[PDB]
Amino acid sequence: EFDEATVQDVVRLAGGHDSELRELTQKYDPAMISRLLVAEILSRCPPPSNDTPVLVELAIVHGSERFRHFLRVVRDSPIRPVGADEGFVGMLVEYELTELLRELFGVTHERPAGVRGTKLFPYLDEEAVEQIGTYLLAAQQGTEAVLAGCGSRKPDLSELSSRYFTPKFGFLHWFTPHYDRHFRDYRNQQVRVLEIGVGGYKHPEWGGGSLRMWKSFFPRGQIYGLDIMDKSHVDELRIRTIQGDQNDAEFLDRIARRYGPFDIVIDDGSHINAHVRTSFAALFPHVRPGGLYVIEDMWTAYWPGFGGQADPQECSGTSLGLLKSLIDAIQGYVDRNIVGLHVYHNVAFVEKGRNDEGGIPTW
Amino acid sequence: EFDEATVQDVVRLAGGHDSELRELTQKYDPAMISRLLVAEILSRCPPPSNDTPVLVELAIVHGSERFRHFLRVVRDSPIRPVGADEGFVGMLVEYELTELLRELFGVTHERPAGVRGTKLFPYLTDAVEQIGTYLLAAQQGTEAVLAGCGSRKPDLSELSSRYFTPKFGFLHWFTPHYDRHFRDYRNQQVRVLEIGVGGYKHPEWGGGSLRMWKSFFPRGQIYGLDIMDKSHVDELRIRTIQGDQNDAEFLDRIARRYGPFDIVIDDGSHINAHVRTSFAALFPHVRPGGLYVIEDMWTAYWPGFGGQADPQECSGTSLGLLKSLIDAIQHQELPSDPNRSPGYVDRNIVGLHVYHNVAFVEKGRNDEGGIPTWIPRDFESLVQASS
Amino acid sequence: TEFDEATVQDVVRLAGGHDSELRELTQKYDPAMISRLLVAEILSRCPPPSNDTPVLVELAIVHGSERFRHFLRVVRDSPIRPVGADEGFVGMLVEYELTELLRELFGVTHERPAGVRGTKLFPYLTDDEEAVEQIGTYLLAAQQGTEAVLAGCGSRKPDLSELSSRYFTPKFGFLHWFTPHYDRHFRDYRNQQVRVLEIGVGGYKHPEWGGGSLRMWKSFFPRGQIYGLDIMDKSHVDELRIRTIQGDQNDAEFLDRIARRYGPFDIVIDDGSHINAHVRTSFAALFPHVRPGGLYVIEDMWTAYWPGFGGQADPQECSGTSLGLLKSLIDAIQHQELPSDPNRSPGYVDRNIVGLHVYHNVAFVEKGRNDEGGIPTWIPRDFESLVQASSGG
Amino acid sequence: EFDEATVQDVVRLAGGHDSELRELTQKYDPAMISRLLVAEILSRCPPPSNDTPVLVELAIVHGSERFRHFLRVVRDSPIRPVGADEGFVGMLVEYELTELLRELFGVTHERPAGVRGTKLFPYLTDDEEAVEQIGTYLLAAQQGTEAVLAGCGSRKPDLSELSSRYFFTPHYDRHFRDYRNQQVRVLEIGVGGGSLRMWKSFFPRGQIYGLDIMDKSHVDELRIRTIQGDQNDAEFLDRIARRYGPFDIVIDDGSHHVRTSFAALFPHVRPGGLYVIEDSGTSLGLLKSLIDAIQHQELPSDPNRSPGYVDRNIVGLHVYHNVAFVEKGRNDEGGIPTWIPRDFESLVQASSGG
Ligand SMILES: Nc1ncnc2c1ncn2[C@@H]1O[C@H](CSCC[C@H](N)C(=O)O)[C@@H](O)[C@H]1O
Ligand SMILES: Nc1ncnc2c1ncn2[C@@H]1O[C@H](CSCC[C@H](N)C(=O)O)[C@@H](O)[C@H]1O
Ligand SMILES: Nc1ncnc2c1ncn2[C@@H]1O[C@H](CSCC[C@H](N)C(=O)O)[C@@H](O)[C@H]1O
Ligand SMILES: [Mg+2]
Ligand SMILES: [Mg+2]
Ligand SMILES: [Mg+2]
């Protein structure tokens, strides 16, 4: 329900100083921004762990206005807003709108206190005693889950991998600690991230796990997912899917001009060797200086059914032949703009930037 | 179970270089060390999220020996060892003994790969229906076990929920302050004393915060003091001690036995006199560069805890102590006096951090020197001297 | 001089954005003027050179078809300054895209070990008989000169203690040992477009001395604006990102005026008169103008023990001292734990302090919403009752 | 001057808790330890900036013992021990012996205060004659103390500054800095011994080894041992690696062989360590093959072929301009399972649910 350009503008202004936050809250309706922040919060919350269901009241305040959201918190259900009559309110959490903007989407130092207000058992007589023993722990656990969603603490990619049912870590692959190392320093930037391959293939429901992972990892980011199949059902706040073929260089240049430039591009697509090579040539020019191009699953370089060759020395048309040529380049556009190559099992990271430093007179 | 002196020695040696790791494995029976590491791993694992129970085989290798442990992993149950046949084995995880020691108890950089070997569905003969049933569960179960085989910093706020301790989420909001002050100690072989194990007179309750410090400090030894017997809490790297925090003689005995402490935390009776007695007796047993923490100063204002409703009538309160520490930090700035001489606390405090219901005191040599004589002692004279 | 304050701040704001903001910037402003602004910043940012032999480092700032060339004369004991192309031996050519230099100096960015610039050693050296002797003469000087210039072209965190000895301030080394505390408390703000107000510019009555600490904060906060308040005139200290203000720190109405004009502040430092009344007046007047999550800093609380600054020799008679203030802030932090009273109303400070850090001669006060809630009435208010209510039988 | 085995033991013990620090100081003469710590300090000190020559007295206390060292600190001159009457004492710095051990060689958090005592102008008496010196020795005593206290800790240095001081580096910093609190063993092949001093400075708890064909025993100092021999003799390389290793880091300068030293020395890099190749067509070929080594578990199964040592032991490769970093570790994650299809269309069908 939120305009993408608007969300991007809110995130841009949130990263600013007091004048930008003020500009933000005058440019847009506060009620609308509050709804946007709650939608963000609900996606950021970890899974609840309390057995007894509780409500956490989230009050967002701007000037004279008070926007109240009653959140149902119980294990095995995602946190959702419900009516005030639908359960026991264990906690009231109050935020100033601009403070919540800073905590969610700002460029901020860590703030261990003073970001909000809290009032325990806010509407609590007869049962006064009995109510404590039933909801005390559940309210502690419910509140912790909501407050976790109200900030920008760095999550654990390996855990997100299990949570969003993506195979980046835990069975087939062990990519996430490499992703963490290469990606974590970008987290306060308003990144644009493009992943080739949303997941689920031709099945009408599956896919998007890795997109949800990047959204969670990059609190200020916009995530784009390209897939040959329609993935419109995956789209949500800060996640856009695009339908098209990674093997169409012209089309890639087109979407890169509309949505770029990209801080990060990830290839987890078809895994056809020619596709990997086409996508790189087409998209590497659209990676920002200081940005990254990632290729997953180079294993197909050894398999003819993906356009590979079993003989590792026959690498001329494979993803590994590309990586090998990137080594030559480091020591054409690509040649002039690569400063680093990181290779791990089934994943490689390419660092973009002018390869122009340390020049000497050849004589 | 496992002898405390031995556990501490293992951790000491595991923090060294190759020669220390070799000394370790030659000094102790490899089989015993493996059981120790598995006990540690069991407490270290996060709660699993897989609905279908799986086994993760952990194989620990040393020389020609191979120690096999089968861990049952399922949501809502603690991870536990079982026999080989007591489930479907979704993953084989293999460690060299010395590598697992480094990963659990070592002083080590982050290692994103190469610390172990993995074999998915290790005993599956090619198997179809088994994929549908177990792939996701194997992935999630392995993820939980592997988290327990490393030293990744946990979230104290989350641990508070998990271990049922009031440090964060309802009554209190301490954990982010603890994180800031404590996280830089995590690669040290810390000794942590908390006064107040929890549960009071209840026969089973308590120890949540001790379990929390154990998780946070992968190389630490945790001690918990309580007036009530808390022997049921004791586990690897956690010892409870029965005694009275208001008994200075006893505190000194246990400090000599188990100290010196890098960290002391008072979360005890919250009687103002007790807080002051414990601080005076235990502050000398805090290491230089260490911390003394006082929780729940709220009782300063409450007579039923020895406090006073008037914040100015603070001479016997925990806040009165904290206020006096400010003067202690500044003590070298007092005008010259041949009669007066600085006390132990004066000479040994270099920082005070006060937050709502929690305060951190930095132990260290307070000997920077006061403002020299030649700097004028009135405003006007200072202005004319600096021009 | 040429660089309007609102312009500098706008440049810094846009530099912190993504590609669309960097493009917006270079379209909003003349690329040549921006390039001049960046060079002015770079000259202030460079460390002292160590090379004995003077070299030229050519900094070329490229934007589209335009190439803005600056020849920087670099030598030990002299401030790096622009000279003519022919006024030395060019040891190194350093080349930046305009938008890339903007990101590096004023942006919010991850560490980039490579790929931010191009360099060419001895760019104009002709293959001659003199060339061999010229390489012997200039090789070391070229690398040392380049190091000094490259350090000024980035936002790498400086050592605070080093900046103390460089700009001649007593924050560390002899009288005081403040810098490691300042580093601990200030380093997490370095990404932000901070506004920092320091009361007490330095130099006192002397018409030349002072500004040392202000230059220290400018260097430490790459994206910041620094304000210095002093009763005396300090107009000579003013430079890019540093403004001085003339006035009394003990005049509350004036403080509220300047805070409304230049605030709100992420950080306020009191290093002024050290008069006990002045510290108290300033805190009450300026604390409301510290941003939530910001810091109020008090230096030199040693004068609290001395009548000549309105202090008292007896530490117990602290009602009017800076130490008395710090003591009361502990109660302010704890105020929600007070027994309820209909007539008592929590004050502004009560509601807005969330932390206090006290070190020898320096204290840091954390501004934020103090509204965690006090211990509920239904928690027993005596130890024996607590034991009973917590033992479940 | 100081026995190598002893230095390593001191460093090992200093990295422990209280019981190790006490064991250290009861195992060795405190006077000797003090002299070792001073030697270390002098090598860690940055170049002084003060024009006026001043003395900094470093006093090291252990029980009844008090070891007093007067250090002349002047611009354009290295800091050295002198007598008390060889200048003006502008500052007395005092450390507990165990505290100095921790600060220099310990595994410790950053401690912004309370690690020492300091007394400015510790011997200046009277008032009328004192004013004269205060004006001339104030600025110098601040700059002189700064330089000494800088050498008294384990703060990370700037490799770029070190590279000029001892007559590219940002990549070294990236990959090396996480090792700094470990008692590392670093071997550099190809040795003036400027770069060995750089690594000594960068790794405060480290032992550095430099191999060269020339005799470079004049480069040897605390925590730096040079080794003479042939780097093309693979047996020799294996021999010295067993003797002095295993190595957390090996640095191989290929410009002045690389395949030979890599094959011989890679097995002696610790798991989780680094093999570094600086600079040339034979170097590049090796780097490219290391990609296949990383990916070796993805090869189609072959009974006649079995993975080599390198295949099983490389887990990462980082290539930059003129330098590459190879990560040693167990490469045993498992290849893609047989039951995953080996052509695109079959893969699409098998993971589309219907
Ligand atoms: N030629 C092509 N162009 C674009 N997408 C393609 C393609 N061929 C296959 N794909 C898509 O690439 C996806 C590979 S699976 C991606 C997995 C996902 N990144 C995750 O981690 O969960 C499939 O969904 C498939 O539909
Ligand atoms: N005089 C005394 N000496 C030691 N412990 C005491 C004491 N009086 C009370 N206690 C103990 O202090 C504890 C307070 S509750 C401690 C809670 C625990 N730290 C947690 O965070 O979960 C109770 O277990 C009580 O038995
Ligand atoms: N009432 C008042 N209001 C504002 N400034 C005052 C003042 N009384 C004194 N000052 C100024 O405060 C300064 C104290 S010295 C400041 C030192 C400087 N902050 C540094 O660290 O380098 C003097 O320059 C003096 O002119
Ligand atoms: Mg993949
Ligand atoms: Mg408590
Ligand atoms: Mg001062």
Image (spheres, coloured by chain):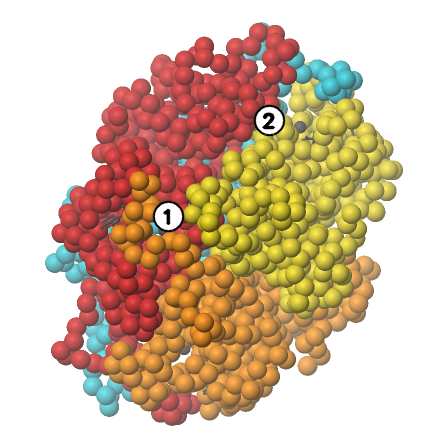
Chain colours: A yellow, B red, C orange, D cyan
Q: Secondary structure at mark 2?
A: loop
Residue drawn at x 28%, y 36% is: B203
Q: Which residue is mark 2?
A: A173
Q: Give the image location of residue A141, x and y in percent.
A: 50, 43
Whether residue D277 is situated above or below residue D290 in the rendered picture: below
In the image, the residue with mark 2 has its CB under 8 Å from the nearest atom of ligand 4: yes
Which is nearer the eye, B310 or B328?
B310
Distance between mark 2 and mark 1 Cα atoms: 32 Å
Task: Using a 10 Å C-alpha cutoff, classify the residue at mark 2 as few (fewer than 14 neighbours), some (14 to 19) or many (20 or more).
Answer: some
Q: Nearer the viewer, residue D211 or B56?
A: B56
- Looking at the image, the residue that sits furthest to the front is A126
Whether residue C370 can be seen here: yes
Query: Is label 1 in a helix, a strand or a loop?
Result: helix
Give the quarter of the image for residue A17: bottom right
Question: Quick one: B39 or A308, which is closer to the camera?
Answer: B39
The answer to which image quadrant residue C11 occupies is: bottom right
Chain on which label 1 sits: B
Amino acid identity at mark 2: His
> In this figure, which residue is indicated by the disc labeled 1?
B185
**Does D234 sit above or below residue A52?**
above
Q: Which amino acid type is shown beneath numbered disc 1?
A: Tyr
Q: Residue at left 59%, top 67%?
A: C194
Provide residue C209's location: percent of width, then percent of height: 48, 85
Q: Quadrant of the N terminus of chain B?
A: top left
Image marks 2 and 1: residues in contact by CB distance under 8 Å: no
Q: Position of residue C137 (x, y in %)?
A: 55, 61
Where's residue B26, x and y in %? 27, 24
